Image (cartoon, coloured by chain):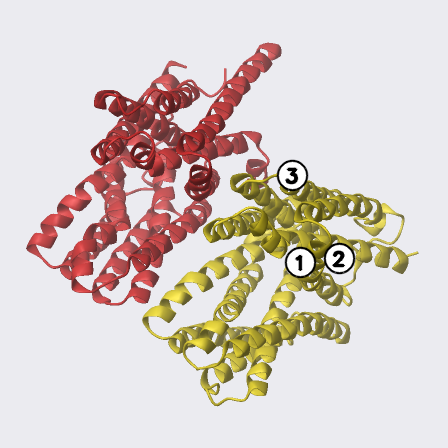
Chain colours: A yellow, B red
Amino acid sequence: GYGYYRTVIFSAMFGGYSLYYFNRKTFSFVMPSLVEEIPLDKDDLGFITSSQSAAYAISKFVSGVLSDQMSARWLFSSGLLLVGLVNIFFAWSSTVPVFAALWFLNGLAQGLGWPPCGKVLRKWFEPSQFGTWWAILSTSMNLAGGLGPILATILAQSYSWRSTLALSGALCVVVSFLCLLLIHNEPADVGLRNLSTLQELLLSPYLWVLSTGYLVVFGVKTCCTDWGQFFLIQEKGQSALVGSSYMSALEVGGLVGSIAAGYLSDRAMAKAYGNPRHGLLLFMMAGMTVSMYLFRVTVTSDSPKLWILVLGAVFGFSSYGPIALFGVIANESAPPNLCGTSHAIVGLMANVGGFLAGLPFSTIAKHYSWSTAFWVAEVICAASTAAFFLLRAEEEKRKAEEE
Amino acid sequence: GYGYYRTVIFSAMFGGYSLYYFNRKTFSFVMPSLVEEIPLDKDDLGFITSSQSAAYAISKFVSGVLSDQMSARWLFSSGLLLVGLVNIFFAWSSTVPVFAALWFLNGLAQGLGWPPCGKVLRKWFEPSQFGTWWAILSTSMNLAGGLGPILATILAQSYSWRSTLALSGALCVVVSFLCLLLIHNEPADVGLRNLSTLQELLLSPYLWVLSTGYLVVFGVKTCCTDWGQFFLIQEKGQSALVGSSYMSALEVGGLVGSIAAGYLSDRAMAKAYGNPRHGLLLFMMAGMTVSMYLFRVTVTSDSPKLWILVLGAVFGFSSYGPIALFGVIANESAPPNLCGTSHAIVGLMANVGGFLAGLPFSTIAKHYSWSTAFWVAEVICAASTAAFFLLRAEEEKRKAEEE
């Protein structure tokens, strides 16, 4: 069949990338038993996570470029196999430089995992159904992060942490061979109807304007997601429960934002003057700017908890959503032989925006104020969003001048 | 004439890149007057230098790729003009986030400076004279770092620090217009005899084996240059004078290593079975491995100061030298329309090796020992160097099998 192989491959990629993000954060999930068995300094823990972050930052770009030419099935399954073998080796090992070297190799394979899912979603799902299944496969990450600490607590209650990571690695080995058996790269590999130069991709201005948009939106995400609790504790007198519930409501709004961004974007593609995935994208960046303004101005010590959770969920709907849409458009606006390169350049701008939003935002927050820092992030977001509204208005004027 | 325009353009690039590295480190040179006028935390100083380091890391690659297509004269002079305008704006400004934003823009333009010098040295100097003038133009950086604190002390004694950076920025503006007037891109732009795809460059294995060699050599450089004083204070009982004089002798040996690497490499190109710039390169990586072995084993608390300065100078001759040769070969083994891309990928591996050698080497040093950490770096260096000797022996066997 056609939809049969579609749902078999999507369930295989769902389970595979679920075990990917389960092993992207397994050390963070198993941290209490590991620090109970052997003492590790917090600088060592931050270094192990930072080595994974640097390896995953490199391996996003390297995996996109290498997933352009190589087959997506073997590359996905080989990465998940390396993930499993790394977690087995992590269960065998008992020291911090070997923990960091193995977790660096895990960061490499975690980067190796996703651009095959992007290539297979592009080959199997038409653009009327590409965004919503992109969104479901990207909230496989959210399901893995939700069932991570729960299964970590269950396996720490029942088993040791050694056997927990050994069973996680063995499960990722078995599911890597199952994703090698189940996933197919294109419908031409079975017998179904299968549905430019790299300099032309790099010299295309739409890739770079999408790149700067993803820079701004992921920087705003990283700013608020890393410093919203600090903005509510230190300046506006909110409790730690309010900041923690703000982050939880922002993540719930982000789940809803990814899913609704994919579905409403595919509804916009189906009902259709430019890319139809922009009418949700720019309206939702404008909603992100409105949520930042309402969160910076109207939140006070006397603000109701319901209103600050509403602003958290509205920002989560409006920041995770445009990032999911930038992933969809970056995989989609490129040619099929260069789509991993486009999504890889977008992930490179994720790394640039994460750097620009982590530490310089803390410096603007330390020297001026927290409100002045989020005002700077709001000025960047509002200026960029108004610039994109001017760009789509200018493109509509150009397309009117064509006809 | 021909040699007349050659020496005019080389003196112009010498003065220009000298003012580049003078303004890459002017904040580090003017630090005492700046912290006397306004108090800055050491985290803020490390953040300003780290923002320059990240911007320079990005701008190496971006400037190589953009110096492939764009003209080298305008790009060099525009970068030096942005350097001057940034230092003037830095003299006008009086706060830490604006210091960091301007110094980020300075890191961008400092990255923008050098790949035009690489392109112009490739267009004007033949390969029998390319390496030695590469070496002299790269020790313009050493001359700038040597005359940096001296002129900083003189201008802090005579003038303020505001007017010091204002005169530095004004001098870089004037010298940017002079480097726009004096430098020429190619000999065809005057009337003299002027002497492949990017996928073919990326898929070439020689670029990637040169890439991994530069990874190893710059990692070994960064390891010993950042942790030799720590290896001599904490483990081997040497004084702080011995560690400081070790770093000074390693930098003097590095000056000699860059100059002698360029000159002996061009002598090897002139006397000539493979690239003739390898017989010095691999012998000198082997000398780097021998210097690391003799520094790890034979240095003790009872070691003479002359012997440890000899090992510092022998490592400096043998680590800065292969990095200068990797720069020469990366600019040279690529086609002239893609040479900045090759040197940009090599600078990307400078960033990867700097990350891999800064903090994980500190972790191996903290958990095992300092001697075990430099033993790990020595194992990486010796394994890589023996692998390159096996590669050139295998290539000589292949070229014997051809004829």
Marks 3/1: CA–CA distance: 38 Å
Marks 2/3: CA–CA distance: 36 Å
Q: Which chain carries label 1?
A: A
Quarter assignment of residue B286: top left
Find disc 2 in the rendering and name its residue: A121
**Are both tags, 3 and 1, on one chain?**
yes
Find disc 1 in the rendering and name its residue: A331
Label tally:
3
Q: Nearer the viewer, residue B391 or A182?
A: A182
Q: Which chain carries label 2?
A: A
Marks 1/2: CA–CA distance: 9 Å
Circles 1 and 2, Cβ within 8 Å, touching? The answer is: yes
The image's mark for residue A92 is 3
Which element carries disc 3, helix, strand or loop?
helix
Which element carries disc 1, helix, strand or loop?
helix
Residue A52 left/right relative to B16: right
Which element carries disc 2, helix, strand or loop?
helix
- Disc 3 vs disc 1: which is toward the camera? 3
Q: Which chain carries label 3?
A: A
Q: Nearer the viewer, residue B250 or A94?
A: A94
Q: Residue at x 28, y 55 (%)?
A: B83
Can residue B367 be seen?
yes
Q: Which of B168 and A76 is in front in this view?
A: A76
Q: Which residue is drawn at 60% across and 73% down?
A: A248
Q: The disc labelled 1 sits on which kind of residue?
A: Asn
Q: In which quadrant is the C terminus of chain A drawn?
A: bottom right
> Is A67 situated above or below B385?
below
Q: The disc labelled 2 sits on which kind of residue?
A: Leu
Q: The disc labelled 3 sits on which kind of residue?
A: Trp
Residue A115 left/right relative to B68: right
Q: Which residue is farthest right? A: A1
